[PDB]
Structure formats: C-alpha cells, structure tokens
Length: 223
Ligand SMILES: N=C(N)c1cccc(C(=O)N[C@@H](C(=O)N2CCC(C(=O)c3ccccc3)CC2)c2ccccc2)c1
Ligand SMILES: [Ca+2]
Image (cartoon, rainbow, N blue to C red; front, side):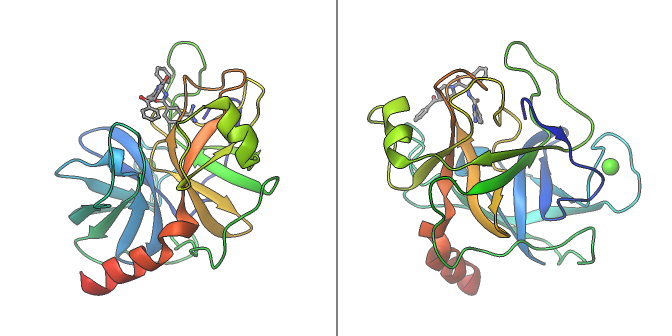
C-alpha cells in the first residue's frame, strides 16, 4: 500500500497473508475453510497465515494453515488478467473469533464513488521498494467505469473496476495482490493490477467480485 496508514493489530480480521517461505500475496477469508485471492497469486505449497499484524514476529493470534486446494478460475487469462480470482481451501478450518473472521460476499455490485478499504503488506513506495512489517490500509473510492477505461484503454473488462486516486500518491501495489477491497462490509474487489503504483492517472484495477458470487458458492459446494 502506498500513501495509506497502519491499520492497527487485527482491525482487518479477514485479511490473510499467503506465504511460500515469505509473504507474496494477500487473500480474504470468506468462511472458516476458504480464502479468496487473485489467480495470478497461484502457486503450489501455499501456507495461509490468518490473524497476522506484524508478519515477521509471532505476536499471538496467528493461525498458520496449509492450503489443501488452490483453485484458479477456469477462464483466468494471464495475458489480460481477466477473471483474476482464485479460491483456496484450507487443510483444516481456521478458528474464528474477533481477530480472525470472515468477510461477507456482495449481494449486489458496488457503485462508482463508494468508499472502500484496501489493505495488505505490499510495497509502501511508488518509486523503489519498502515492505512493511505491519498491515497497511488505504481508504479509496470506486471510480466510474468510463474514467477506468480512459485510464487503461482496451484493458478494462466487465470483470474489473478501478479504485483509488487519479492522483498519484495513494494506491495498492506489489505484495498487496490478491488482497481485499471491502466496501460497506462486503468483499467487492481483489487487488489485481495497475501500471506502476500510485502513479498519476493510473489507478488500481481490481477483480469485480460481485460477478463471481455464484461461481464461488458452487465451487465451494463441490469441493
Ligand atoms: N498499482 C496497483 N494498484 C497495483 C496492484 C498490484 C500490483 C501492481 C503491479 O505489480 N504493477 C506493476 C506494473 O507496472 N505493471 C504494469 C502492467 C501490468 C500487466 O502486465 C498487465 C497485463 C494484462 C492486463 C493488464 C495489465 C503488470 C504490472 C509494477 C511494476 C514495477 C513496479 C511497480 C509496479 C500494481
Ligand atoms: Ca505475526
């Protein structure tokens, strides 16, 4: 996250870290056994870390659970990032409390101008690199689809939305990928991609989770 703030320990309790000997992506807990993340975060041997604040110190509240299954949407296209969504099943159910909790899925799509919360342990710089120990947060609005498409001509599908500041200065970034965009208590986006981070007229682009609710529910039902 570039230009955001320290969330505070366990204030975003659905936020997980995907680890492969190091933090590589975020994810969102949607029930005790399943996490939503980006398909471009796929890899074998994922370890899901729930209840994290500082990802480098065991502080208490952590739960480390191996992924038993990592399911990339079947129409995911790595060239375009269309359908950039992945479902991870945990080997054992996480224990849910106030520091580890699920985030509800949307019952409808969100509208342009709605304010959302985006978080992660990704790069905090727009130039160069700096990775934080503690979870960072950023409040950002959903942009209109016309402004989204003018910023990224021919690259925005109906399964994507832009959010952030046309700005420069405040955005998600590498390392935050797969992580949540939560708006009025619903998981409406997945950190997916953008040109650089926090650059003027290049806002973040997020998977549009309201288009995948039936797919998530059927995939979970079958697995
Ligand atoms: N800012 C966000 N909100 C955000 C969030 C999460 C990751 C990234 C991210 O990693 N940004 C890349 C970048 O410049 N690129 C451009 C094109 C994109 C791509 O190849 C593509 C492919 C198909 C369709 C659309 C885009 C791949 C990343 C990058 C490279 C070097 C330093 C910083 C950032 C950005
Ligand atoms: Ca920790």
